[PDB]
Length: 174
Image (tube, rainbow, N blue to C red; front, side, top):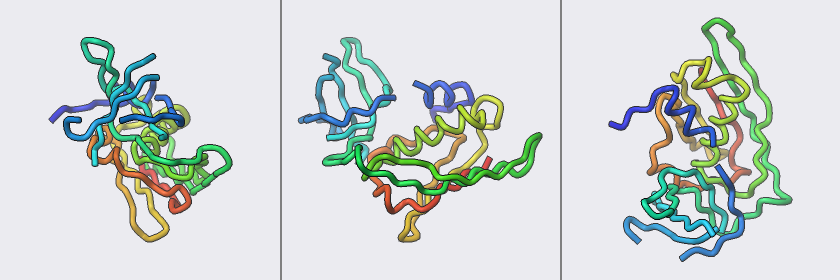
């Protein structure tokens, strides 16, 4: 029901902070910890992917999903193939290259957010390119995830965790 246009999406997937050293402790399953910034995380279903959704009347910053327990961020490197495809329009291109992930396990939230942010900077998504696009993230077991670019990621998919090794290719269509 809450509609998101190009401007709304662009503003969300730009301005993000990884906290890879937390020990946190609620309504619909939430956690609380300081950073002296008092933070709360909603659990859609310690390393956390922090994206500000809301800041309460007295300085309690809210985010959704992103929390991964016992994760290695240094020493590990997964490079699945990112295949970008804009087939019809003013400038039609195909572009395949490795998408570097320096994390053992990665939340769908971060992969989505960081992947979209990349399409804004380099290809001009939600700026010069249309918001009308899809993304398929294929795993080695043949399973996959679908990101619709027309709307921002539904909160109830941000609690999903992904083994970085298991990702083989990310297919973006514009």
